[PDB]
Image: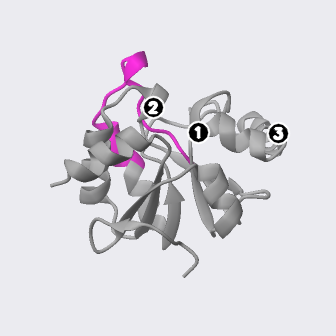
Amino acid sequence: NSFSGYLKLTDNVYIKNADIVEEAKKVKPTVVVNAANVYLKHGGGVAGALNKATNNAMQVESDDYIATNGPLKVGGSCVLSGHNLAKHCLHVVGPNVNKGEDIQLLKSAYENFNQHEVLLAPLLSAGIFGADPIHSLRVCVDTVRTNVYLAVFDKNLYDKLVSSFL
């Protein structure tokens, strides 16, 4: 299909060193995953980058969602518009280890991916959420059964994830 340049890790998990924003703009996937928080406040990390690329439309939509439905749970998700990036955005809340949230909820977070056949996604709970990216990749592989294309921004981290994969 339109996903190009990925390394195959398993039957269903693929990985690339790429900026998820630039990869979404090129591919226009059906589903892009956002690394959200429970308030859908898209300030930094992946969320801030995705929101910026939508010219803040993602944040306006998200504020309406929260006003109607209240916060998400850690491990939970919602499906909103993908704006100019994708058909849909799956906002998924992984645990934030810097807030003391339970790392076991990472598995629950990845289970949300199984409701969608194909996804472009970041590693959940990595980056500013404080979890070990090697662990996040392992949980992903062991949990997700649908086709997931992972975009890893940092080249040094990408190389470490590939070279330590087991």
Query: Which residue is identified by label 3?
Result: 56
Q: Are marks 1 and 2 in contact (CB under 8 Å)?
A: yes
Which residue lies at the image location 43% right of the left edge and 66% below the top edge? 6
> Which residue is the site of mark 1?
46
Magenta part of the chain = 91-109
- Asked if the magenta segment contains residue 107, the reply would be yes
Q: Is 125 on the left-hand or right-hand side of 72?
A: left
23 and 121: which is toward the camera: 23
Can residue 98 be spotted in the picture?
Answer: yes
What label does residue 17 carry, if any? none
* Residue type at the position of mark 1: Val
Position of residue 56 measured from the top left corner of the image (x, y, whole percent): 82, 39
The amino acid pointed to by label 2 is Gly
2 left or right of 138? right
Residue sitting at 41 percent across and 46 percent down?
Answer: 109
Q: Are marks 2 and 3 in contact (CB under 8 Å)?
A: no
The residue that appears at 58% across and 39% down in the rendered structure is: 46
The mark that comes first in sequence, 1 or 2, is 1
Where is residue 94? Give x, y as percent. 44, 38
Front residue (pair 40, 6)? 6
Q: Is residue 155 above or below residue 151?
A: above
Furthest-left residue in this view: 166
Residue 164 screen position, x and y as percent: 19, 47
Q: Residue at x 37, y 47 (%)?
A: 158
Q: What secondary structure is marked by label 2?
A: helix
For marks 1 and 2, give the CA distance. 9 Å
Q: Is residue 157 a member of the stretch shown in magenta?
A: no
The answer to which image quadrant residue 113 occupies is: bottom left
**What numbered label is drawn on residue 127?**
2
